[PDB]
Image (cartoon, coloured by chain):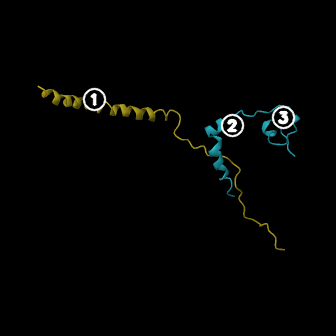
Chain colours: A cyan, B yellow
Protein backbone atom coordinates (compact mmCIF):
# COMPACT_ATOMS: atom_id res chain seq x y z
CA UNK A 1 0.00 0.00 0.00
CA UNK A 2 3.08 2.22 0.19
CA UNK A 3 5.03 1.49 -2.97
CA UNK A 4 3.33 3.97 -5.31
CA UNK A 5 5.05 6.83 -3.52
CA UNK A 6 8.47 5.25 -4.08
CA UNK A 7 7.71 4.97 -7.80
CA UNK A 8 6.50 8.59 -7.63
CA UNK A 9 10.09 9.58 -6.88
CA UNK A 10 11.62 8.20 -10.10
CA UNK A 11 9.08 10.20 -12.09
CA UNK A 12 10.57 13.37 -10.63
CA UNK A 13 14.14 12.12 -10.84
CA UNK A 14 14.09 11.03 -14.46
CA UNK A 15 11.00 11.70 -16.61
CA UNK A 16 10.64 15.47 -16.72
CA UNK A 17 14.39 15.78 -16.14
CA UNK A 18 16.09 17.46 -19.07
CA UNK A 19 19.61 16.04 -19.04
CA UNK A 20 18.39 12.47 -18.86
CA UNK A 21 15.86 13.19 -21.60
CA UNK A 22 18.75 14.59 -23.62
CA UNK A 23 20.78 11.46 -22.91
CA UNK A 24 17.85 9.36 -24.13
CA UNK A 25 15.66 10.50 -27.04
CA UNK A 26 15.63 9.07 -30.59
CA UNK A 27 18.63 6.84 -29.79
CA UNK A 28 18.78 3.29 -31.08
CA UNK A 29 15.63 3.50 -33.17
CA UNK A 30 15.22 -0.04 -34.48
CA UNK A 31 11.55 -0.19 -35.32
CA UNK A 32 11.08 -1.91 -38.67
CA UNK A 33 10.01 -5.43 -39.51
CA UNK A 34 13.69 -6.15 -39.19
CA UNK A 35 12.86 -5.56 -35.53
CA UNK A 36 10.68 -8.65 -35.84
CA UNK A 37 12.70 -10.57 -38.41
CA UNK A 38 15.37 -10.65 -35.70
CA UNK A 39 12.89 -12.57 -33.55
CA UNK A 40 12.62 -10.19 -30.62
CA UNK A 41 10.48 -10.93 -27.59
CA UNK A 42 8.84 -8.10 -25.60
CA UNK A 43 10.00 -4.65 -24.73
CA UNK A 44 12.12 -3.64 -27.73
CA UNK A 45 8.88 -4.77 -29.36
CA UNK A 46 5.60 -3.29 -27.97
CA UNK A 47 7.44 -0.25 -26.66
CA UNK A 48 8.00 0.24 -30.41
CA UNK A 49 4.76 -0.56 -32.19
CA UNK A 50 3.43 -4.09 -32.15
CA UNK A 51 0.98 -4.74 -29.34
CA UNK A 52 1.34 -8.39 -28.27
CA UNK A 53 2.28 -10.36 -25.15
CA UNK A 54 1.74 -13.96 -24.05
CA UNK B 1 -8.07 -24.49 9.21
CA UNK B 2 -5.49 -21.79 9.96
CA UNK B 3 -5.19 -20.05 6.60
CA UNK B 4 -4.51 -16.54 5.43
CA UNK B 5 -6.94 -14.23 3.71
CA UNK B 6 -8.88 -11.71 5.81
CA UNK B 7 -12.62 -11.19 5.58
CA UNK B 8 -12.05 -7.45 5.21
CA UNK B 9 -9.67 -4.55 5.60
CA UNK B 10 -8.28 -3.25 2.31
CA UNK B 11 -7.27 -0.11 0.47
CA UNK B 12 -6.14 -0.31 -2.22
CA UNK B 13 -3.24 1.94 -3.07
CA UNK B 14 -3.45 3.87 -6.30
CA UNK B 15 -1.80 3.21 -9.62
CA UNK B 16 -2.02 6.92 -10.39
CA UNK B 17 0.59 9.50 -11.34
CA UNK B 18 0.24 13.14 -10.28
CA UNK B 19 2.34 15.99 -8.88
CA UNK B 20 1.70 18.95 -11.22
CA UNK B 21 1.87 21.85 -8.73
CA UNK B 22 2.18 25.27 -10.41
CA UNK B 23 4.25 27.02 -9.53
CA UNK B 24 4.19 30.75 -10.33
CA UNK B 25 4.56 30.48 -14.10
CA UNK B 26 3.56 32.31 -17.25
CA UNK B 27 4.30 36.11 -17.15
CA UNK B 28 4.55 35.95 -13.36
CA UNK B 29 8.11 34.87 -13.98
CA UNK B 30 10.05 37.24 -16.30
CA UNK B 31 8.30 39.94 -14.23
CA UNK B 32 9.87 39.31 -10.83
CA UNK B 33 13.19 38.93 -12.65
CA UNK B 34 13.15 42.27 -14.44
CA UNK B 35 11.66 43.90 -11.36
CA UNK B 36 14.60 42.63 -9.31
CA UNK B 37 17.22 43.55 -11.91
CA UNK B 38 16.03 47.15 -12.28
CA UNK B 39 16.24 47.51 -8.52
CA UNK B 40 19.92 46.62 -8.87
CA UNK B 41 20.84 49.30 -11.39
CA UNK B 42 18.74 51.77 -9.42
CA UNK B 43 20.95 50.84 -6.47
CA UNK B 44 23.78 51.73 -8.80
CA UNK B 45 24.07 55.44 -9.82
CA UNK B 46 23.62 56.24 -6.12
CA UNK B 47 26.90 54.58 -5.19
CA UNK B 48 29.02 54.64 -8.37
CA UNK B 49 28.07 58.26 -8.92
CA UNK B 50 28.75 59.07 -5.26
CA UNK B 51 32.14 57.36 -5.27
CA UNK B 52 33.04 59.55 -8.22
CA UNK B 53 32.56 62.59 -6.00
CA UNK B 54 34.85 61.31 -3.26
CA UNK B 55 37.33 60.37 -5.99
CA UNK B 56 37.79 64.04 -6.90
CA UNK B 57 38.32 64.87 -3.23
CA UNK B 58 41.13 62.30 -3.19
CA UNK B 59 42.80 64.06 -6.10
CA UNK B 60 42.02 67.38 -4.41
CA UNK B 61 44.42 66.84 -1.51
CA UNK B 62 47.15 66.05 -4.04
CA UNK B 63 46.74 69.28 -5.98
CA UNK B 64 46.53 71.59 -2.97
CA UNK B 65 50.06 70.48 -2.16
CA UNK B 66 52.98 70.04 -4.61
CA UNK B 67 54.18 73.41 -5.07
Q: Is residue A5 positioned above or below B57 on the image?
A: below
Q: Earlier in the sequence, mark 2 or mark 3?
A: 2
Disc ID at residue A30: none
Measured as percent of width and height from the top left, residue B16 is found at 69, 48
Q: Nearer the viewer, residue A34 or A15?
A: A34
Q: Which chain does the numbered disc 1 sit on?
A: B
Residue B45: which quarter of the image? top left
Residue B66 placement (x, y as % from top left): 13, 27
Identify the residue at horizontal 33%, vertical 34% (top origin): B43
Query: Mark 3 — on which chain does it sit?
Result: A
Q: CA distance from mark 1 to mark 2?
A: 52 Å
Q: Quickly name the residue at label 2.
A: A24
Closer-to-camera residue (A31/A23): A23
Percent across and percent down for residue B31 are: 46, 33
Where residue A20 appears, as percent x and y from the top left, is 64, 39
Q: What residue sits 63% from the left and 49% below the top?
A: A9
Please state which of residues B4 and B43 is positioned toward the viewer in this rendering: B43
Taking B57 as reference, is A32 left or right? right
Q: Residues within 10 Å of mark 1 (few under 14, many from 20)?
A: few
- Could you tell me which residue is drawn at 81 percent across and 39 percent down? A46
CB-based contact (under 8 Å), mark 2 and mark 3: no
Instruction: Give the label on residue A35, or none.
Output: 3
State the separation of the CA atoms marked 3 and 1: 71 Å
Q: Which residue lies under the disc numbered 1?
A: B49
Amino acid sequence: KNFSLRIDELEEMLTNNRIWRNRTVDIGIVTAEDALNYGFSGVMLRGSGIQWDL
Amino acid sequence: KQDMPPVGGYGPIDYKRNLPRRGLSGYSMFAVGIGALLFGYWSMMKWNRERRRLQIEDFEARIALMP
